[PDB]
Image (cartoon, rainbow, N blue to C red; front, side):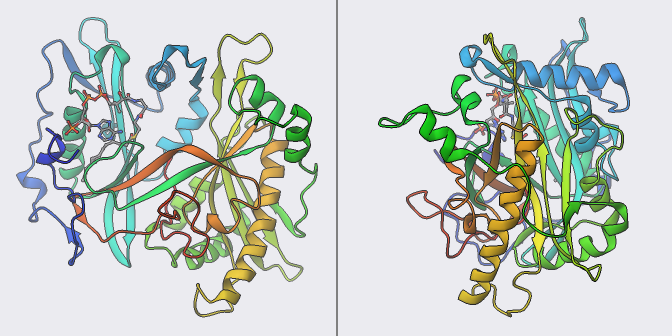
Length: 422
Ligand SMILES: CCCCCCCCCCCCCC(=O)SCCNC(=O)CCNC(=O)[C@@H](O)C(C)(C)COP(=O)(O)OP(=O)(O)OC[C@H]1O[C@@H](n2cnc3c(N)ncnc32)[C@H](O)[C@@H]1OP(=O)(O)O
């Protein structure tokens, strides 16, 4: 499908199979002065609204809307379980504005029925510094589906961001839209097999007993990497530089500021185990040097119609970095690769141990970054979904997603996608 995109055919996006030769903005430059200060027209019975994350009730309508409508099928037996903690983390990064957390409420009932948010970030695209925004959490109520409300949400958010002189954005989607700059596959590492099976999230291959599977996926109780501990504010300067250094190898990344970095990796203090969102770890050597860093975040699902379970823990491998190959000049030097693979397999194995001990039931990871070096060895099984990466108002050459043409993990090129979207 290439011409049947009534809305996207009108937007400044790359075209399918387009041979990019000059990367960069698509539309001719504009000024925030050429941008209407008035919110786009909306269906007579609807009205725009600005969700204040700092408001209990308002933030609540957001995750209630998303929880009830994020899954496409009432018979699924499961639902997303966004929390106030999750959104406080994801929506309050430095530079955020209530004006960019947009919703659509029914005038009469004031019911939230749509939502979409943007957060400002600096994107690094093949070395190019691009002030942008990341769009996420787009959601339209099930009763308002196939009515083409989405394009209006997109256009209204594009306007508010443009009025602030920001002209680009990164967004991801499982569905195929005009020219993705990259595609990655999802993988799942069973941490609590028995429960995943009982809530029907994994199968039992013919020839295998439930005992085979449990033993096969059984994990040690304690981590193994020496010097491994939780990230602390004291560590920020070192970890930040280590991260930036490692990240520079990728072609698509978010260029954090120390402030953004700290907000993103050290969560809200005083949160119970069962409510904690971000989990960041570091490895410190006897000389005080920080040589490793990895993180994962929690986003549970609510389980339905089950007498034994009503919640499913889901950990998502996030950002990480290590100096394991800083000794070699060329990332793809087979020696640099071997050294990096051995370290990542070690660090991420401990990550699975930490996620399981944190009561995560399954561990999710994409084939982005250098993930394919450890994915198969650490038993992250091939998932059924794929994630396409896109750039609004920006034309860029294709970036490796860590997949072979047959959808298997490309362990030799890995991926040049360094950003991890929520
Ligand atoms: C510089 C500043 C710019 C900032 C803006 C950046 C732009 C990018 C922002 C995009 C945010 C993405 C980041 C995330 O949050 S991706 C996560 C989105 N959420 C979910 O997948 C879970 C729940 N799903 C829903 O609520 C769906 O029903 C949605 C709302 C997604 C579609 O509701 P609906 O089924 O009732 O469709 P429609 O009748 O309103 O309208 C259909 C039109 O919209 C296009 N469409 C559908 N889904 C997506 C999607 N995920 N990205 C981009 N476009 C999408 C579609 O191709 C069609 O246009 P066209 O093919 O005919 O031309």
